[PDB]
Length: 241
Ligand SMILES: O=C(O)[C@@H]1CCN(c2nn(C(=O)c3c(Cl)cccc3C3CC3)c3cccc(F)c23)C[C@H]1O
Image 1 (cartoon, helix red, strand yellow):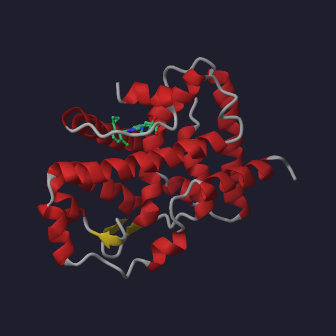
Image 2 (cartoon, helix red, strand yellow):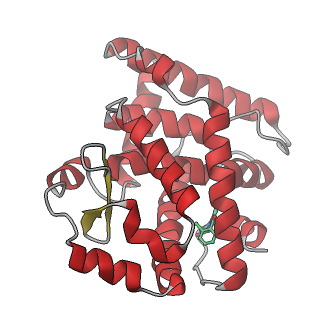
């Protein structure tokens, strides 16, 4: 009715559509866990075979976030520079948050290539400090027992941030940010879930995790470059140089 309630449906639709899997499908598969036979298979793989697999799962992940951003109200009406600046900075932060859905805090596993498995599965990659942080972030986000609308509005907020450096129409972004802040506050009140606001991770934590992540990603792309069919080419030319 109040148009903010409309935006809540809009942002929840976008997220529902741009989701790879469904929460119940990820929840039921918690039983189907990789055997040591299969874990060893992964550990034994080349660093580069594992890098190719992981790189494509990540480019796929980013492509759904790019589609989610496209489906957000008034995102296209922004200038390409602002679309770049927002997406370059936040798309992977959204991927990191989205990841807590495929993470099981009981066995400390993640749903990868059809089954749930631990961080050891990634030994071949040789970046244990980073993988542990990723798994640690997802373990803290797991505690919030985030609902699907809660992840939707939060990730839309992660993306839409007027504080990003390099915005040419900061004011046009602030207007989008503030409606989403209302949408999220409103929704949280309606459902008696505002308690999560205090439990939400600090902005700096997320940006630090992401930067480390994108650095190891940029390092591997220099060594063993993968090829991706760009959903947003001016972003691709920016990230992949
Ligand atoms: O248009 C598309 O389909 C592209 C998908 C990959 N993508 C993005 N990749 N990306 C990466 O860290 C990444 C990934 Cl995931 C896989 C391989 C190599 C890299 C590093 C060289 C950058 C990023 C980080 C932060 C924000 C983003 F957008 C992207 C750009 C998009 O334009």
